[PDB]
Every structure is written in structure tokens, then in C-alpha cells.
Length: 4
Length: 4
Length: 124
Length: 124
Ligand SMILES: O=C1Cc2cc(Nc3nc(Cl)ncc3Br)ccc2N1
Ligand SMILES: O=C1Cc2cc(Nc3nc(Cl)ncc3Br)ccc2N1
Ligand SMILES: [Cl-]
Ligand SMILES: [Cl-]
Image (cartoon, rainbow over all chains, first blue to last red; front, side, top):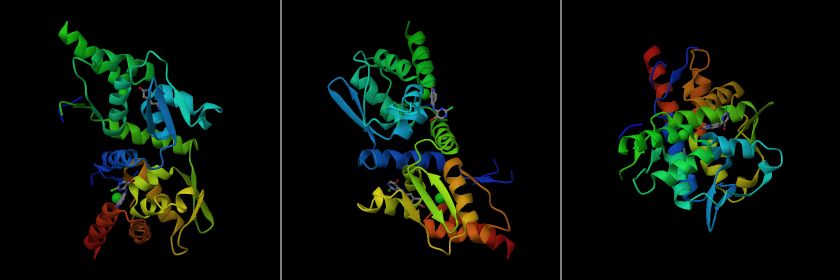
């Protein structure tokens, strides 16, 4: 999971 | 396009 | 093999599938969550959820145009997860994390359940 | 928004769609290319091809279970492109590049046409  |  | 790969292809496919969803094109099922209805593509639901995979591979249920979810399922949690399925983006907030995790466990969306458990463990 | 994103989600969705294709699950159309038949999902074809997008958004053609392609279309070129649609991998070879490019132009698959033109320009 990432900060888009 | 890339070499997978 | 000696194949070449187009990096953005999977993302572009999903973006187009979401555009079809937004315009209600070739949607083939309604998911009923209490008083709410959500139109979707059976294939996308199966590709994202262990529960929908099991439902639409069933010889009788594969032909249903309406699927009713357990009454304990929150429509907002379902909406957030349906958006995730079609976009890879999860709108996870302190106010919805419990409903989202409960819905992801029911739908059998392991990666969503994992990030929910981690975000909850951080706040305790 | 304040969304988080699961990097591998789009790739995992496409992998699952390809698994459904391999087991012939919920395929809803046959594409006829001369003496050959290819089963697929209308939504995936539309998401990858400007030609299939136009065909399946047509109020009459959207309901067809069989689509016949132009007789000039090579079945191997089509097969290679159908595999690409479901995997992001293109099996481009000196022996098939002309058929693949001609098929990609007909199907309106701009990124495939672009790499074919570049690979051809390099060999001249
Ligand atoms: O957390 C998750 C997400 C998910 C998706 C599917 N979907 C499919 N799985 C397989 Cl093996 N083949 C085709 C399809 Br469609 C099955 C289980 C799970 N569990
Ligand atoms: O080279 C390409 C690939 C492609 C795909 C689509 N598909 C869709 N396009 C739009 Cl805008 N909405 C929903 C869908 Br499905 C249209 C045109 C093209 N040209
Ligand atoms: Cl997931
Ligand atoms: Cl393309």
C-alpha cells in the first residue's frame, strides 16, 4: 500500500 | 514497454 | 518466453472497466446491501473477492442478476470496497475503518483486511 | 482525496480475469477469425480495443454472442493480441510483427501499433  |  | 510488457496496461484496463461501471455499460448484476443497490460486472467482482468468486462459479448462482448480502453488511463499507475493486484506491478513514474491515472479511479481500488490521494496531 | 492505493491491485485483477478466460468462466462472446474461434469477456475486449469498445456500445451489436472479424485478419495475430489484452505481455517476433501490427491497427490498440512501428523502424 502507498500514498498515491 | 519493458523486458519483464 | 521472449515477450515484451506494457507497464501501464493493467492500470489502463481497470480504468476503462471503471468508466464502463460509471456509465452503467454491460453491468450484469445488482448487489443489494440493505436499502441500497450497486450495479457491477460479475467478472470484476470475482477478480477482487473470494466471496464473489465462489458465488459466480456456482452453477445456480452464476445466473442470478440480483445478489443479496448479509443484513449485517454496511452499505457505505460495501461502496468503499466496490470503488477499491475498480480503482485500487481505498478510502480508509477513522470513521469507516471498522465497517470496511468487517465488509472486507465477509467479501474475502485479504489485502484490504491486512491494511485495516495494521491501521487499527497503530491507533491502539 | 486521502485514499491509500494497493500497487499490485490492477495486475492481480487482470491475472484473475485471465484465469477466468483459461477456464472459460463467464466468457460471453466468441470472436471468429476465419476458421478459428476465440472465447472472451466483452468487457475486457472493450477495455483494450477501440474497435470492440465501438462494437459492444452499439445498441444492436452489444447483444451478439458471435462477432465475425474482417477475413483479412490473421488468426495468429489475433491470438497474440488477445493474450496481450489479458496479460500485458506481447509475443512480438520477426515472423509475426507484420500480422500483429495489421491486427492492432484494425482493433485500434494504439500502444501495440506504436511498439510495432518502432521495432520495424529499427530493423530497416
Ligand atoms: O482476497 C482475495 C481476492 C480473491 C479473488 C479471487 N478470484 C479468483 N481467484 C482465482 Cl484463483 N481464479 C480466478 C478468480 Br476471478 C479468489 C479469491 C480471492 N481472495
Ligand atoms: O488503443 C485503444 C484502447 C482503447 C480502449 C477503449 N475503451 C474504452 N474507452 C473509454 Cl474512453 N471508456 C471505456 C472503454 Br471500455 C477505447 C479506445 C481505445 N483505443
Ligand atoms: Cl484485496
Ligand atoms: Cl494497446
